[PDB]
Amino acid sequence: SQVDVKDCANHEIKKVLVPGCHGSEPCIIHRGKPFQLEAVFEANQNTKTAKIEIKASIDGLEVDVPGIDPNACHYMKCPLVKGQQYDIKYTWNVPKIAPKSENVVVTVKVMGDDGVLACAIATHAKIRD
């Protein structure tokens, strides 16, 4: 369970499941490029909305667009009050061999009602031998 991934906001998370690695290990990319990230993180304040923003740098082709819905407030008892667990998710399929297993690192974060909520990055996905 859990994989290496790293936080980029403020240890305000708890679990981030993404297709690729599963721990300190090394995981390449099985071709076919879908981006499905799912994470749980408690809220540390009050808020009536929380968007989602994926920032992915894939072999010089850093994508800069949203591939899903980022406001689960139209999906769950809004507004969200502090201490309440909040899980965000994203899943968008894409060309099977567009990016070049070499050099891609994704960092996606959910921004609540004040700008921030839970953010986690991931990488381990290149090509060699």
Image: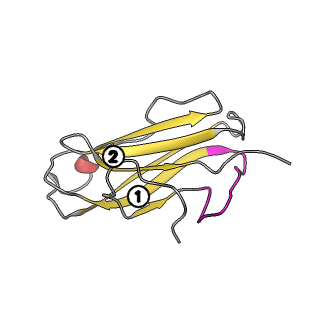
Q: How many marks?
A: 2
Image side of residue 49 versus residue 58, left or right: left
Estimate the x, y position of residue 128 in percent, counting from the top left. 81, 46
Q: Is residue 115 visible?
A: yes
Q: Which residue is mark 1?
A: 39
Estimate the x, y position of residue 23 in percent, counting from the top left. 59, 66
Disc 2 element: strand
Estimate the x, y position of residue 83 in percent, counting from the top left. 19, 64
- Reply above or below: 3 against 96: below
Q: Nearer the viewer, residue 64 or 7?
A: 7
- Reply above or below: 57 against 20: above
Task: Please rate how many residues cluster around mark 2, counting C-alpha atoms within 10 Å: few if below 14, some from 14 to 19, many from 20.
Answer: many
Disc 1 element: strand
User: In the rendered structure, which segment of residues is drawn in magenta?
Assistant: 19-33
Instruction: Tell me the kind of residue under disc 1.
Output: Ala
Q: Residue furthest bottom?
A: 1
Task: Please rate how many residues cluster around mark 1, counting C-alpha atoms within 10 Å: few if below 14, some from 14 to 19, many from 20.
Answer: many
Q: Residue at x 34, y 58 (%)?
A: 11
Q: Residue at x 56, y 30 (%)?
A: 62
Q: Nearer the viewer, residue 59 or 71?
A: 59
- Reply above or below: 111 against 2: above
Q: Which residue is mark 2?
A: 110
* Image quadrant in which you'd find residue 27: bottom right
* Image quadrant in which you'd find residue 34: top right
- Reply above or below: 126 against 20: above
Q: Residue at x 24, y 47 (%)?
A: 74
